[PDB]
Image (cartoon, rainbow, N blue to C red):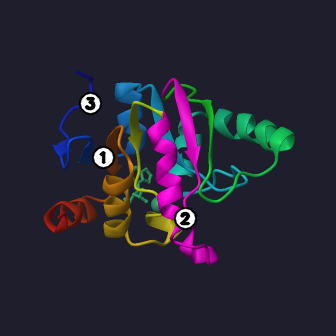
Amino acid sequence: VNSFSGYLKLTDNVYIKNADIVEEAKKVKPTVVVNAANVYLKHGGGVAGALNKATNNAMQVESDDYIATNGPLKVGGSCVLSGHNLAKHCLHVVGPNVNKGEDIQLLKSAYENFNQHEVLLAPLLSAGIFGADPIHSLRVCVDTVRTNVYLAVFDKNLYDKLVSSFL
Ligand SMILES: C[C@@H](O)[C@H](CO)Nc1ncnc2[nH]ccc12
Ligand SMILES: [Cl-]
């Protein structure tokens, strides 16, 4: 039993809700919140910009030190950093950005990072401003993640579309 509330159950381990991931994280304070990161951990817009803003830019400061030490992530890769005031940990995961020409096949690799954590709050990877089809992202999530994932979909219209089309 966990403290996530109001989610629709899609499969044994995948759940979905129309919600602002920032407000969800502030309420639940999960062990792991997933950020829709880029390889430079530059949290400018979309989920990343919103999460970072909610940390008063502390996420960006921590991320800049991470990059200065380790260099960029790989597309499909991840790193674990602090969750600041939002969660215990933030799993920064880089899905392919279609608006950059990156290989959508890497979306499965991106979701594989979730399997290293028993429970996560997360967005749909490569959706939104990353330019991939969210219906496809949800399908890859369900077919790749085996741990317990609570998906927050900001757009109510898209949420209704994802549920009604879910196979
Ligand atoms: C891009 C997809 O992940 C989804 C599409 O609606 N975007 C979001 N989902 C949840 N919380 C969010 N906070 C800011 C953006 C956002
Ligand atoms: Cl977005």
Question: Which residue is pictured at 38% across the width and 63% down the height?
Answer: 137
Res 10 seen here: yes
Across and down, in percent, residue 153 comes to 32, 53
| Marks 1, 3: nearer the viewer | 3
Q: Is residue 150 left or right of residue 37?
A: left
In this figure, which residue is indicated by the disc labeled 1?
Answer: 19
Give the residue type at disc 1: Ala
Across and down, in percent, residue 92 comes to 58, 44
| Marks 2, 3: nearer the viewer | 2
In this figure, which residue is indicated by the disc labeled 3?
Answer: 4
Res 154 seen here: no
In the image, is residue 114 part of the stretch drawn in magenta? yes
| Marks 1, 2: nearer the viewer | 2
Q: Are marks 1 and 2 in contact (CB under 8 Å)?
A: no
Above or below: residue 166 compared with residue 55: below
Q: Give SS at disc 1.
A: loop
Pick the residue in front: 159 or 133.
133
- Mark 1 lies within 8 Å of ligand 1 (Cβ measured): yes
Pick the residue in front: 29 or 15.
15
Q: CA distance from mark 2 to mark 3?
A: 29 Å
| Quadrant, the C terminus | bottom left
In the image, is residue 2 part of the stretch drawn in magenta? no
Mark 2 Cα shell of 10 Å, populated few (<14), some (14-19), many (≥20): some
Mark 3 Cα shell of 10 Å, populated few (<14), some (14-19), many (≥20): some
Give the residue type at disc 2: Leu
Q: Give SS at disc 2.
A: helix
In this figure, which residue is indicated by the disc labeled 2?
Answer: 106
Across and down, in percent, residue 75 comes to 64, 60
